[PDB]
Length: 43
Length: 162
Length: 97
Ligand SMILES: [Zn+2]
Image (cartoon, rainbow over all chains, first blue to last red; front, side, top):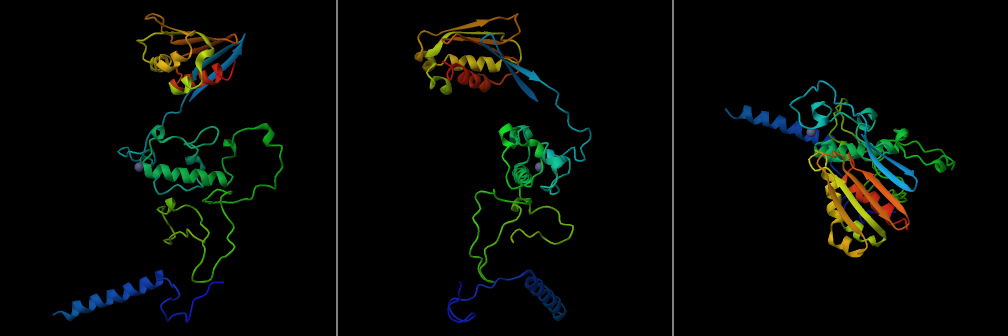
């Protein structure tokens, strides 16, 4: 009774899918790794 | 507590003031420096709708919310105590503070549906017929967002909507 | 004094207010007086006489009213709130008659 016109993930109307707390965790973990990376890449 | 006494005698109506004894505040508050009654007793971000002993200290004999100028609560805490008190009423606690009408305990109704943490009033809610799929969902509110600042011992933040 | 003057005060015979000004608790009765002493209230009934009696020694604020159904209303000011007196006054002196 609710449709997602066309294909789910492609067009100008997409499925709304939300960001989650898990995803935020992962993103931040990976950032922290990069920060530590360029500290050691500096000198 | 000021009781107002009234008499009808010999076609004369007599009205008179009467002062009973109010309890003085407890001897030694943990945060004497503190401003608002919740805070010096160190109860901020702690009480929930479940704590009756705390809520009852602000309300009226017939069940309504007490005014703020008399209580003197930090505005934040006043709205919180309102929502808490309403949830407490709808949760069928404080059965003493319902107003007393004799005709009222006559009319049998299907025994009160036990509910708790109810945000809205029973009347105004409309049954949600449409749900909706994984991506757009209608959510049923539980508890009030005013209480979102309470301490979490689980470390896990509360679910306001389901 | 709106709530009183809106109710058509014409049904009153005599209003006497006895009070003792130097007592710390006076305000309410005084407030009541000034709501009786309003222009519109007094303009409704020209048959109603308002007498203000002041006593230093008495120590008891009191308000007495008479109205046409043969009712004598005595309210004893001690701890009574200002708006309460005007409130009970409206339901007693208007709804009755
Ligand atoms: Zn406070």
